[PDB]
Length: 258
Ligand SMILES: Nc1nc(=O)c2ncc(C(=O)O)nc2[nH]1
Image 1 (cartoon, rainbow, N blue to C red):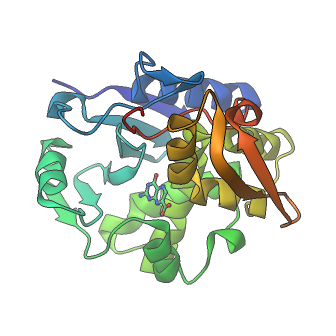
Image 2: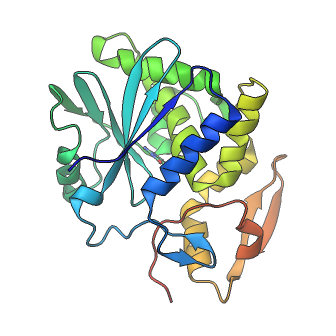
Image 3: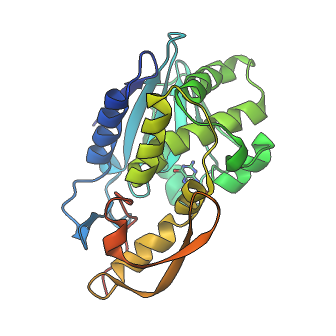
């Protein structure tokens, strides 16, 4: 009757504490009973009961502020958030999703649905910057938490709210989806660095649906046609088999098997 909550703080964050956080997120996103070619699948949206539909990620910072994100277990998407007495949700893509989000944060005094949706393309337009120009790392996360916290009081400008959602989505949902992206965030934390995601990260994020489909329709792991990804330097290279992606992709959106 209460969605599971996973907590993380940027205060004193370490490689280990962030690893533990991502590990716990993945364990609440899916039971891992459905696995294809060794890669776990998230639950199928079709028929999933509303009491199993979301998980909550509570984020706190050194500035002593806390916000709670809500993630959809079917796709790990961030659907909205709460900060004390206000909660905000991206505009839903359909009436069923609009109904499902009514079961989030039910006791909050003030609820709002943004005019805009939450996909990267729309967020980047609102932010005035692409993912490739938005730094990630503990420093960015601590600032995003504060920016989300102050939004209900009028203190946070919309382009900074959208930048702050882009940071959270990549450092939580994308890291859950891809060990490679989790590793990129671990490296930033290890060296107290803040830097934008390189093309390898961006193209993996953009490819998640396509890779979920290609792995799940594969012939014993062999892709039906090669998929082009980007190296760190922006060069394209082909992948032909799920085997090379085992240490890279952690979760997939559901597809029916062949
Ligand atoms: N809100 C949100 N949560 C996500 O996990 C997410 N992940 C991917 C994309 C995207 O490809 O455009 N947008 C997202 N937006």
